[PDB]
Length: 174
Length: 174
DNA sequence: TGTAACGCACTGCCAGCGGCTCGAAATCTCTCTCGT
DNA sequence: ACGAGAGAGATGGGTGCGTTACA
Image 1 (tube, rainbow over the protein chains, first blue to last red):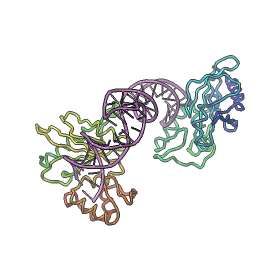
Image 2: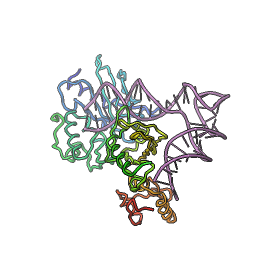
Image 3: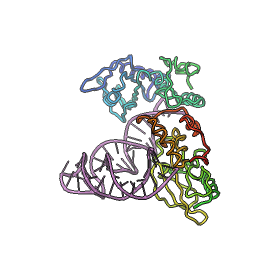
Image 4: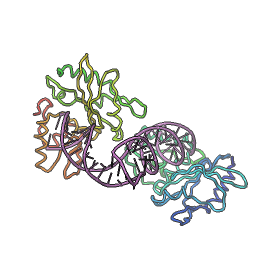
């Protein structure tokens, strides 16, 4: 278990210490393409895990980034790993804290943040509401029939207002 | 053999009693998606078999519907059975009668109905007409040089008229 | 005119490198448990 | 509401004939 302040710290320590192994090449992860999500982004007092979203530019990389992820100077086991979700246990200041990692591509970014910020109940209200208008929403995008609806948006705020919903900051989503 | 009357009785009996097994689930076939075809849709006095065209929504389901087909409370053996055609022998009022089932995916429905309605001598006239115009028509769609000619059509009638042919009632095709 | 189910011969190509079996080795689905 | 990872369960060589059978 953690506190908000500690989690923010850990998030700061990792922005600049991220890289994955690709054809024997250790490629850096720009902090520009790392977004914190989960109970942390919803400025909660007490945490459980830390969740970060990693943005991947090129489709072909997905198989390489999460399974072969590297962190400078930190001890970390691994519980499960896929291309899209990863669960690590790290040691920080001599203690064990769960860390969760996720992955989205450029045009998935707004949908991805909005999905992973949450919280659940808020997602559930939203997705149900658009289900009654024949849409499906997920972390990938908006879909009407099979075909994914292309939306002229770029930011999460932009996306929410496009989905015709009051925009609230993350710590007021229920 | 069967009287047309006995045939209508059977189809009607069957409409609300068709289901298949799919992952240990017994899935009800909607009478909405059960078309009667062959000699019975052509309203012949004397029938030899009973022909049922079943409409399957999701292509993935073809390998489950027909091979795991069940009929609530009616004896039947199975002569042959595959994904697309399946041949039964049922006990009805202490007599053995042959029942055929065929399948069609939603977007084939017009061609299928048209196909299975028959009769053969009619289809030949028709297919041979579209052949000399470099087409092939079959239960699955219309083709030109191995390429599916898409048509915005949704009924057997629309299809026939789109094909440029005088619509005849099923009982008047020869 | 146009297609399906099925049993089969002839291979082709892996588990088996000789067999055309049973059931290996690798790949699928589904089911479960998990996330937000 | 809508997806993921990881086991479990299940498949079991491709062709292409020829024959019977469907409208």
